[PDB]
Image: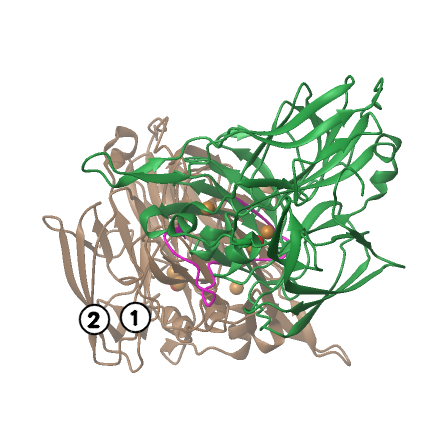
Chain colours: A green, B brown
Amino acid sequence: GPSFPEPKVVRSQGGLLSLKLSATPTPLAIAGQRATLLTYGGSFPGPTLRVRPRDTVRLTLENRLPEPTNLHWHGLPISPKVDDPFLEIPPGESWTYEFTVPKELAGTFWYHPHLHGRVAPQLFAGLLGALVVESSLDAIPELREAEEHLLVLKDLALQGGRPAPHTPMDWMNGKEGDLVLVNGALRPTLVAQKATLRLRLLNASNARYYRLALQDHPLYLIAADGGFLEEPLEVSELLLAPGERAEVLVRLRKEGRFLLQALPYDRGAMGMMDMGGMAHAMPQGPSRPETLLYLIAPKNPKPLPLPKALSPFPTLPAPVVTRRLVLTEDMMAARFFINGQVFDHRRVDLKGQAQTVEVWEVENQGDMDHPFHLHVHPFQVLSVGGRPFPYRAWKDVVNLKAGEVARLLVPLREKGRTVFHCHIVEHEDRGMMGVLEVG
Amino acid sequence: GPSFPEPKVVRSQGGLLSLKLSATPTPLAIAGQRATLLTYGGSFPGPTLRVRPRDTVRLTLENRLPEPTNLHWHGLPISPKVDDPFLEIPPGESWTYEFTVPKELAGTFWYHPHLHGRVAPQLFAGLLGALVVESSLDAIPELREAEEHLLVLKDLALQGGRPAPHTPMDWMNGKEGDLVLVNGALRPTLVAQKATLRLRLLNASNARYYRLALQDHPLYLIAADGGFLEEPLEVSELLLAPGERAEVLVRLRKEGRFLLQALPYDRGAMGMMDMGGMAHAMPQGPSRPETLLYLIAPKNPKPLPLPKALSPFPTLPAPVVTRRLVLTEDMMAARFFINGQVFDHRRVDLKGQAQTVEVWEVENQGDMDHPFHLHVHPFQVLSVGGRPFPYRAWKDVVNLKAGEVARLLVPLREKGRTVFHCHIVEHEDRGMMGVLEVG
Ligand SMILES: [Cu+2]
Ligand SMILES: [Cu+2]
Ligand SMILES: [Cu+2]
Ligand SMILES: [Cu+2]
Ligand SMILES: [Cu+2]
Ligand SMILES: [Cu+2]
Ligand SMILES: [O-]
Ligand SMILES: [O-]
C-alpha cells in the first residue's frame, strides 16, 4: 500500500452520500499485532466521509455491539433532532441519520458514539471516523497544489488482544494508551512528494493531548475545529486537545528526515502515592515525548507561497446574554461538575433564543485541563486565560488549563435540546455535561 | 387654613412609622362640592408619610370597601413579598405591611391600590397618598432654605356626588376628569414666602398627563421618580406621565402672579365619529390647557444659588442580558399587550438573577403614549426614541410615545415575583402587565 496509511475515503455521489455502516467487534491487525476492536465499517479508524456544502448525507448505522450506541456528528451545525445526544440504538437495531450539509461550512469534522455513561469505553475501543467538508477555497492554487493528508491522532492500550479495560484511575483521569498511533498505524513514514503539505489533524483520543511540533519547521495554521482562519497563522507548535481539529500547511525547507512529535505536556493527570502515612493524590506530571510519524522531504523542496487570505470570518450581531459555567472536580470520587451539578438528561440548564448571540464565560476551577465542547452551535473563542485569541475561526472545543477562563461568542443556530460537556469523555460519562435548550 | 392646601403629614417617630389606615367611602367637601370618595385616612389625597432611610414602616391597612384591595408601595425598592402585587385583602379584613426603608434612597414615592382588574376605578375614586423619603442632602443650605411643598396632580369627574363611572371608552383611553386638581383643591393659590421653592411633584392621575410650565420661569429638575439627579437640570417645561414624580427648584424672578399650567399635550387618546358611512376611531388631539395653581411671588425676590451638585449616580456593573418588551394595542377591544400576550398571574414572563444588571428595551408599537412601570427594581433611563437622556437618576416609570423605544439599565434587587405594566391603569387592568421573577 501507500507508505502513508490513511482511512479509506467515501465520497458523496451526485450530491448524495448514502451509506450503511455497522458498529461491530472486528478482528484486525494493528501496530503489528492481532486485536479485536470495535469499528465502524470494519476499519480503524472508520472510513473518512468526504462531502461538499448542500450535499445530502444518509447514513444508516447498524448496531452490532452488545450494548446500545448512537452517533454524534461532532462539529456539524445541524439540528439536534438529527445529531441527537439522547437517542439510543439498541443492540441489533439500526437508525438512519439524514441531514443536509450547511452551505457556509468547511473543514475537518468527525463522528463517534455519544450514549451517556458508555462513551469512553466505546470511543477507546475504536469507534470513530473523520468527515471532511470540501470547500471552493480548496481550488485556490496554494492549497490545490499542496499534498493533502488526514492525520487521525488516537492512542490505544491492548490487553489479551482487546482494548484494555478502564480502571478507576482511568475514570478519574481519562484513559491514555501506550500505543500512540496515527491513522491506526505505529509511527508511519510519510514520504512527501511535494514541498508543501496540507495536513488535516484530528485528536480522536479519549484524553491524550498532542503538543505538536515538527522538527526544524514551523506550522502554518489555516483552519480550526470548524472552519478556516482569515489568513494563515505561523506557529512553532500546536496543542490539540481531545476532540479538537486543525489544518496546517507545512513548508518543507530542505531534504532530510523530520520527526513530527507530541512534545511533553502536563494536562494535570493524577496518580496515587504512599510515602509512610500518605495514600494521597500526586501529579503524574508531563507526558513522555512521543514520535508520531517520520516525515521525509523530497529533493530540492521549493514550497508554494502561502495563500494571502483564506475565509473572512462573519461579523456577528451584538450578544444579548452572558453566561457563566464553572467546572469543578471531585477527583477521588471521579465526579465532575458544571455549576455544581452533574448531568441529568431531564434537566434543562440553559435556555437560549435561536439567531441571537450569547457570550459564554467558561471557567476551569479544577486542577486538570478540561476541553469544553458544545454541540450544534460553533463558537468564536475571544480569549482564554485573559489572553486574546490570535485568530478568528469557528471552534467547537476549547481547552482550559487549571484556573483559566475562556470567553466565547456563541451564535445560537438550530432549535432544540442539545448538550455541552468536557471532551475528556470519561469526565462526560462521569457527569461533566449539561443541557442547552434553544427555542 | 394655609392658603396652600397640602395633605396632612405623618412622620416616623424614633425610627418607626406605625400607622393604621382605613380604605373607606368618605363624604367630604371637594372643589366646592360635596362628594363621597374612596379615601385612605379619611382624606383626599391620603396622608403624606414622611420617613428617613433605615426607618421601620408598619402600616396596617383596614379594608372598608365593598371589594377587595391592596397596596403598591410605588417606587420603593423593597421586597415583593411585602410590596405584593398578588395579595388580596378582602372587604372588612386588615393586613400589615412592614418593611425597612432602604439606606440609599431619597425622593417622592406614593401608595395606591394594585388589585388586578380593579385598579382604575379604585385609584380614580381617590385611593392614593404620597410617601417622602428625607435625605441628608435636604440639609444643604440651597435646599434647606427653600420653601418646600408637595403637589399631588390628580383629576376627577363627579356624577351624582360620587366619582363618575368608567365607560367603555374610558377603559380604552384611560379615564380623565374635568376637575383638574392639586392636592384635591381646585386651582389653589400658593403665596410664596421665599424666593426659592422646592416642589415635589406627583402625577397620581389614572391617565391624564401634565405638560408642566410656569409662566415666565424655567424649572430646575433636581430629582426624578426615585432619587436625585447628579446636578440640577434647567428645563423650560416638564412632562409628568401617570405614576411619575419629579422634584424641581423654582427661582422666582420678580414680583407678580404666575400661572403653573398643564399645557396642551396629545397622548393619543381616541374618540369615535360617524361622517356618513363611518363609525371609526378618530384622534382626540391635544388636551385643553389647564391652570393648575396661581403662584404669587414675594416682594423683591432674591432666590438662593442653585446647589452645584446633588447626588452622584451609582456606577453600575456591566449588564448580563438584554430584553425586548413590545407594547401593542387592540383599541376597539380595549385590550393591551406585552409581547403579544395579556397578563396572567400564573405565568412567569421573565426570569432574572438578583444583583445582576439587565438592559431592557421597551418598544411602543401602539399609537397611544404608554408609561411603562416596573415594580421593585428602579432603573436608569439611557435613551428614549433614540435620544440620550440628559441626566442620570433612578426612575421607575418611563413614558413612550408612539413608535419610541426606551433603553433602560435595570439592576435586579430583591428576589421574588413581581410585575411590570403600563401605568395608564385602565390598560393594566385590561391586560398590559407581565411577570418578572428574580432569583
Ligand atoms: Cu466529539
Ligand atoms: Cu474534563
Ligand atoms: Cu458531545
Ligand atoms: Cu403606581
Ligand atoms: Cu398604556
Ligand atoms: Cu404596579
Ligand atoms: O462527544
Ligand atoms: O401601580
Query: Which residues, given as a range, are shown in magenta?
Result: A336-360
Q: What amino acid type is highlighted by mark number 1?
A: Asn
Q: Ligand 4 lies in which image quarter?
A: bottom left
Work out whether residue A284 or residue B307 is closer to the camera in this orientation and state it: A284
Residue under mark 1: which chain is it in?
B
Residue B95: which disc? 2
Give the image location of residue B65, x and y in percent.
Answer: 27, 79
Q: Who's the residue at 61% across and 29% down the image?
A: A261
Which sits earlier in the primary sequence, circle 1 or circle 2? 1
Check disc 1 and report its element: helix, strand or loop: loop
- Residue count near mark 2 (Cα–Cα under 10 Å), binned few <14, some 14–19, many ≥20: some
Work out whether residue A63 or residue B274 is closer to the camera in this orientation and state it: A63
* Mark 1 and mark 2 on one chain: yes
- Quadrant in the rendering for residue B18: bottom left
Residue B92 appears left or right of A383: left
Q: Who's the residue at 74% across and 42% down the image?
A: A5
